[PDB]
Amino acid sequence: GSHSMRYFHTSVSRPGRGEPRFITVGYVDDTLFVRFDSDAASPREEPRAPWIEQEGPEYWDRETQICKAKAQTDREDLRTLLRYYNQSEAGSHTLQNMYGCDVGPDGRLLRGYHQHAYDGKDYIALNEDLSSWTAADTAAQITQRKWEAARVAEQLRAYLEGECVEWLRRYLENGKETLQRADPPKTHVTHHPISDHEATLRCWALGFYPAEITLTWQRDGEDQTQDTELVETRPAGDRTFQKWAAVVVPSGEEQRYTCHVQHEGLPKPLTLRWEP
Amino acid sequence: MIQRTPKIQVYSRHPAENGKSNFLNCYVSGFHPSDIEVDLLKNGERIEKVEHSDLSFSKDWSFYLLYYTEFTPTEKDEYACRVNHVTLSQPKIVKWDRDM
Amino acid sequence: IRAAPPPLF
């Protein structure tokens, strides 16, 4: 289909309780495939999907080395950030990095990413050109200047256009049973009386993969955006996701309301109504 | 220091059928900082040995985690998720409702 | 597969 690969990294300092904890996970689309936690008994990058297990020791050795090296650099960078922001050493701080690539149906690069956040706020991001930077503030500009001096973007571009795309292709093929299978939503509408005067209609979508979905209510064909309660798409724990959308309907109006569902696993968008 | 309070959903993997084994999930999302404490409760007491996902985060940098355990729902047993986070003055308890 | 890390901040 269109597809993505992402690596997520978080270091959280904890002054007086040892060294910062480092956790990194890798995803293809919405499927977790690798993990590393510095607080693990014997930290190694570990597989989380059957299709990666076939990779050889050379792969795992290099992944684990990379993980450990980043834990170390993140610790140095956390120290640097205290200086850049004129901060005390007493508090816990957070440093995050996301990078990866999006590819289209033909396997060609659509977009690459490489960006960081400090204490939950944008710090520095590689622009879509894979050649220039956006620094959030005058502290990040210090890093920008160093990274421009060292031609960092050129090195990241090479990865994002190269190994990122090629290895994502490989994973898609090795994991084609699951990664290239869309599970459509199982859908139904439920009715929950609130009072004599009104009831909730809740439109459910269950057991779908990947997570992207659109769930809408209309009344007399008009979208009910402002009156629809829409929950965040949530993991079921069996690889699939769930979502619902609910509206409060006056008694006897239920047939004016229609639930509309779009998912890549569906050949045509669905229309549902409450069926007493 | 910006802080974002967790969204919390408590729900089952499969539609609840009394007497049939299932999984109880507590999904916490949209939060910062990452430090958070989550318990799943059965009749007000903490369920032991609950598992959880590894820390990850969304496009806007906010964090998410899934806590989960096997459970067998019944008519009478009450389940809940209890969350603590720096943004909360007291722990937030969200009861499991099989209709949500 | 992962990337080589960038330089320090």
Image (spheres, coloured by chain):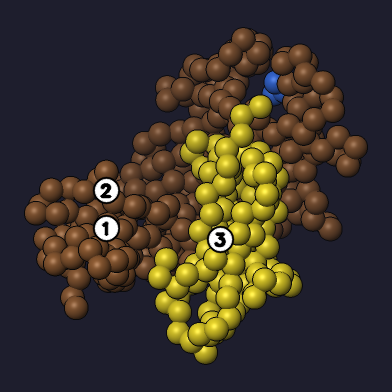
Chain colours: A brown, B yellow, C blue
Q: Which mark is residue A227?
A: 2
Judge whether residue B49 can be spotted in this image. Answer: yes
- At label 3, counting other C-alpha atoms closer than 10 Å, the crowd grade (few under 14, some 14-19, many 20 or more) is some
Q: CA distance from mark 3 to mark 1?
A: 22 Å
Rendered location of residue B74, percent (x, y): 53, 85
Identity, as a three-letter code, of the amino acid under mark 3? Val
- Residue at the limit of the structure toward the left, as seen here: A220
Q: Are marks 1 and 2 in contact (CB under 8 Å)?
A: yes
Callouts 3 and 1 on one subunit: no
Q: Residue at x 49, y 32 (%)?
A: A113
Q: Is residue A13 above or below residue A241?
A: above
Identity, as a three-letter code, of the amino acid under mark 2? Asp
Q: CA distance from mark 2 to mark 3?
A: 23 Å
- Look at the numbered disc 3 and give the secondary structure of its residue: strand
Q: Residue at x 55, y 58 (%)?
A: B27
Q: Which residue, given by chain and number where applicable, does mark 1 sit on?
A: A248
Left or right: A247 in relation to A252? right
Sequence-earlier tag: 1 or 2: 2
- Residue at the limit of the structure toward the bottom, as seen here: B19
Q: Which residue, given by chain and number where applicable, does mark 3 sit on?
A: B94
Identity, as a three-letter code, of the amino acid under mark 1? Val
Q: Residue at x 25, y 68 (%)?
A: A196
**Residue A70 falls in which quadrant of the image?**
top right
